[PDB]
Image: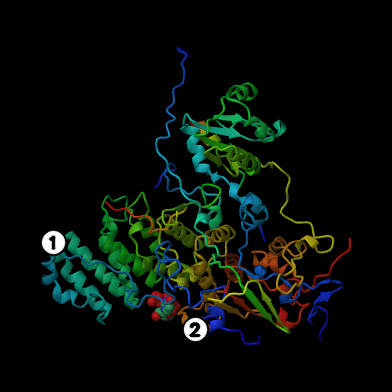
């Protein structure tokens, strides 16, 4: 059901290897040195 | 009973004995995974290029973009030799890989004059295309080094689209068996005890391990060994 | 100095050295550490969860009118977490006799689903007759429009797996996207039982269809019960399905795949007793599941094994 | 067919700014307090004393790792 | 150990689409 146009679709150099999953040349971090690039399930919060 | 292979020897035949657990840089014990079934440039031998890789675009995206083009998405054909290219990927444009480094340093006008189409702005989506997805990757690194924000490589590209089997470069998976002695460039003196010790460069290299690893089919794997079993040169406890 | 090393916490000659904090400096905490907050791990126990229902929940929704009316008949059928030992012949007799008297479709079908589940736990074979007598006409036959209540389907499916029955394939097929679209509502236990049955019967093609749907519907792959995956995979002898199963095996996780191997090696091994029907020999699929496991685990260095025969060359 | 010739407007406005620190900005280093060393004593096989400055020493370090060393007023 | 499984057959993915059109 999820369309080819969705952001869900995973385009990363690698599926398995974490160091190949960045957007830019090094791994950026969010505030508080939290991981940005590939977020873990609980880091994404949908709140009001 | 025992011999040079089985005994503890610092050195065997004038070179550091690779069989000793203590002749290796401890870093060689750290855990790693097999690469080889993954895409060529993800593998560990290309690690110097890893910071550069490109976000993928799959076959689905490609067919979708064939039927439903976006104005400012550009599909750029990287195929190098005209002798091998008989079809046209819809809405594509031709910048052969060999020219890229030069092409991307032209002004908008000059680029227009040399390639006959408008140079993509650095915001626009740029999808790269090749036979196997190798040259498209290298080209991608070029486009990324001039800083282009969306650069996607479509691996398996023209081969998957048109069902052609061609290759950008002739490179084979098999490594030639290592020839000389162990390279002094990999020999690693220790800083505390001043002790010389092997690294996994050279005749000892993970590539060679993965290359000769057990095949993933019982029949083809049994064919590889004599009737009695796989390793009978070793003492039972080393098997 | 010695064969026994100093332990850096208890030794003041480590603790108070220049490379650590002396006891005359001001003793405050150096930097804060937030580990658990930055990147958190999800809980997965090494042991399976102790309270989980471990069966196929049949979802009894009855109107609290017929629920009271039918009580002396239903008291014989399974209620939540309770499995009365009533012989299945009796229960089916009661349904056949009393059900035409009840007017509700929804009630008659909840009741039927209970009967099926009850007959699945005793493995009585004559219960499919009930499917052909009541349900087949308005659900499975000649493109009938009607869409069966979910609980009934789950129950019948569960019965076809518990009693190994060719019938399942006809029902399952109706549950995909173009049919009833019930497949995404299946429990993990549902999939487990299905796979195990199909595996015993030995349909590579059933196994393939089912693994494809499971994957597409986003079943919980890692928590599908290992025994049933192994028995399913063991059933695969055909070249194409075999190919499929390699490519597919990459969908499990590191851990899952390690225990796929362990479980496999046990079921043809020491634990060959654990099965009601013994496995069948697949040397190929066994070898492959082991191989896959080896590929996906972290690799260890045993240099005396790798380089055992290495000789240097001056070429 | 073409009815027209036009000049290509685009809105390039950057008005938002998102900069994210790369990971290595927060990595640890080893930092140290630093005082002027007034003297040093080393002993392993044979004791050796070096005295840079003679004053009443207000602080003293002892360090055992390879050689016994004592850094005075360090 | 590569290739793990038989590569996809030679099938041409563009033709059917442009044929429909
Ligand atoms: O993972 C497990 C562990 C143990 N068992 C236990 O193995 C016993 C016999 O092992 P079987 O797995 O051959 O029996 P079965 O298919 O008839 O059992 P169900 O799973 O259908 O109930 C079963 O009666 C059950 O108690 C499993 O079925 N699965």
- Choose between D67 and C85: the one closer to the eye: D67
Farthest top residue in view: D3
Which image quarter has ligand 1? bottom left
Identity of the residue drawn at 68% across and 75% down = D50
**How far apart, in angstroms, are the residues tagged by discs 2 and 1?**
49 Å
Quickly name the residue at label 2: C273
Question: Would residue D19 be seen by someone viewing this image from the given angle?
Answer: yes
- Choose between D26 and D12: the one closer to the eye: D26
Farthest front residue in view: D55
Q: Chain of mark 2?
A: C
Q: Is residue C56 left or right of residue C246?
A: left
- Choose between B176 and C215: the one closer to the eye: B176
Q: Chain of mark 1?
A: C
Identity of the residue drawn at 22% across and 63% down = C109
Quickly name the residue at label 1: C103
Crowding around mark 2 (Cα neighbors within 10 Å: few <14, some 14 to 19, many 20+) is few
Crowding around mark 1 (Cα neighbors within 10 Å: few <14, some 14 to 19, many 20+) is few
Q: Position of residue C184 (x, y in %)?
A: 35, 57
Do the residues marked 2 and 1 share a common chain?
yes
Disc 2 beta carbon < 8 A from ligand 1? no
Report the quarter where the C terminus of chain D lies: bottom right
Identity of the residue drawn at 37% across and 55% down = A44
**Where is B57 relative to B222, above or below?**
above
- Choose between A5 and C215: the one closer to the eye: A5
Which label's residue is closer to the chain start, 2 or 1?
Answer: 1
Q: Is residue C232 left or right of residue B173?
A: left
Q: Is residue B164 left or right of residue A33?
A: right
Q: Is residue B157 left or right of residue C252?
A: right
Q: Position of residue B109 (x, y in %)?
A: 59, 21
Q: Tell which tag, 2 or 1, sits nearer the viewer.
A: 2
Q: Position of residue C255 (x, y in %)?
A: 50, 69
**Where is B112 relative to B151, above or below?**
above
């Amino acid at each position: 059901d999820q369309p080819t146009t969705s952001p869900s679709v995973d385009r990363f150099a690698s599926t398995t290897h974490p160091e190949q999953r960045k957007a830019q040349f090094v791994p950026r971090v969010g505030p508080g040195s939290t991981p940005l690039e590939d977020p873990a399930a609980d880091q994404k919060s949908e709140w009001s | 009973q025992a011999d040079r292979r089985t005994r503890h020897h610092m050195m065997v035949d004038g070179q550091i004995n690779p069989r000793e657990w203590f002749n290796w840089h401890p870093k060689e014990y750290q855990p790693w995974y097999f690469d080889r079934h993954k895409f060529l440039y993800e593998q560990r031998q290309y690690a110097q290029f890893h910071h550069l890789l490109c976000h993928q675009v799959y076959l689905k995206d490609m067919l979708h973009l064939m039927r439903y083009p976006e104005p400012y998405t550009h599909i750029i054909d990287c195929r190098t030799s005209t002798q091998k290219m008989h079809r046209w990927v819809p809405h594509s444009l031709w910048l052969p890989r060999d020219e890229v480094e030069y092409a991307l340093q032209l002004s908008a006008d000059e680029f227009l004059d040399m390639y006959g189409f408008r140079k993509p702005d650095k915001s626009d989506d740029v999808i790269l295309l090749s036979h196997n997805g190798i040259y498209s990757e290298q080209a991608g690194w070029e486009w990324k080094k001039q800083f282009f924000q969306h650069v996607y490589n479509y691996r398996g590209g023209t081969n998957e689209l048109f069902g052609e089997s061609y290759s950008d470069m002739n490179v084979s998976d098999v490594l030639s068996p290592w020839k000389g002695p162990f390279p002094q460039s990999g020999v690693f003196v220790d800083k505390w005890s001043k002790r010389k010790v092997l690294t996994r460069t050279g005749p000892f290299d993970r590539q060679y391990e993965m290359q000769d690893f057990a095949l993933p089919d019982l029949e083809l794997e049994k064919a590889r060994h004599p009737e009695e079993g796989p390793r009978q040169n070793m003492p039972f406890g080393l098997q | 100095v010695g064969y026994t090393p100093v332990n850096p916490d208890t030794s003041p000659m480590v603790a108070y050295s220049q490379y650590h904090w002396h006891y005359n400096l001001p003793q405050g905490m150096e930097r804060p550490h937030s580990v658990n907050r930055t990147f958190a791990a999800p809980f997965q126990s090494n042991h399976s969860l102790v309270n989980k229902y471990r069966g196929v929940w049949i979802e009894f929704d009855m109107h609290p009118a017929f629920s009271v009316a039918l009580e002396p008949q239903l008291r014989k059928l399974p209620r939540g977490r309770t499995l009365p030992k009533t012989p299945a012949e009796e229960v089916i007799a009661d349904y056949t006799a009393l059900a035409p008297l009840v007017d509700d479709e929804k009630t008659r079908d909840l009741w039927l689903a209970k009967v099926f589940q009850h007959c699945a736990f005793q493995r009585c074979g004559g219960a499919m007759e009930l499917w052909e007598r009541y349900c087949h006409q308005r659900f499975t036959a000649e493109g009938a429009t009607a869409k069966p209540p979910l609980s009934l389907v789950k129950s019948v499916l569960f019965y076809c797996n518990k009693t190994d029955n060719s019938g399942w394939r006809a029902l399952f097929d109706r549950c995909l996207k173009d049919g009833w679209n019930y497949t995404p509502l299946f429990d993990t236990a549902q999939w487990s039982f299905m796979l195990k049955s199909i595996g015993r019967m030995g349909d590579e093609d059933g196994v393939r269809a089912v693994l494809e749907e499971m994957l597409d519907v986003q079943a919980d792959l890692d928590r599908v019960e290992a025994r049933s995956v192994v028995i399913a995979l063991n059933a695969v002898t055909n070249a194409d399905v075999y190919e499929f199963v390699k490519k597919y095996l990459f969908n499990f996780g590191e851990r899952k795949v390690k225990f796929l191997r362990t479980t496999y090696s046990d079921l043809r091994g020491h634990g060959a007793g654990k099965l009601r029907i013994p496995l069948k020999e697949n040397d190929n699929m066994y070898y492959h599941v082991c191989w896959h496991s080896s590929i996906r685990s972290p690799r260890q260095f045993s240099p005396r094994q790798l380089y055992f025969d290495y000789t240097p060359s001056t070429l | 067919m073409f009815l027209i010739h036009f000049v290509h407007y685009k809105t390039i406005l950057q008005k938002y700014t998102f900069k994210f620190k790369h990971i290595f900005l927060s990595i640890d280093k080893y930092n140290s307090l630093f005082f002027n060393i007034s003297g040093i004593l080393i002993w392993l096989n044979i004791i050796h004393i070096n005295i840079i400055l003679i004053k009443y020493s207000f602080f003293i370090l002892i360090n055992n790792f390879e050689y016994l060393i004592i850094l005075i007023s360090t | 150990y590569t290739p793990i499984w038989k590569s996809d057959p030679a099938v041409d993915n563009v033709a059917p689409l442009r044929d429909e059109d």
